[PDB]
Structure formats: structure tokens, C-alpha cells
Amino acid sequence: LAACLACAL
Amino acid sequence: LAACLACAL
Amino acid sequence: LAACLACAL
Amino acid sequence: LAACLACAL
Image (cartoon, one colour):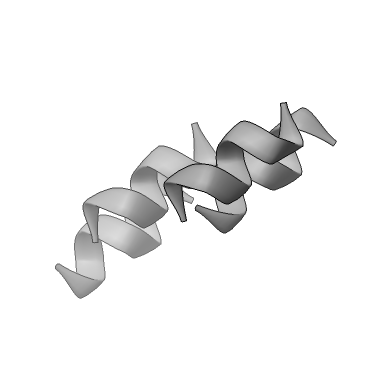
């Protein structure tokens, strides 16, 4: 989940 | 954007 | 290890 | 890059 937030932004 | 980040975490 | 490879690329 | 992935695995 943390990585995907990161990815998004 | 900024606020979205703050929120998520 | 597997995840390290994934990430790098 | 494609070859080094291949190598790795």
C-alpha cells in the first residue's frame, strides 16, 4: 500500500 | 495533493 | 532479493 | 537492461 501511494504521487 | 498525502498517512 | 530486482528496474 | 533481468532470474 505504501509504495502505491508513492507511485501515485 | 499535499493534503491528500497527509491524509493517507 | 526478488523484490530488490523488481524495484531496481 | 532486458538481458540483466534475464541473467538475474
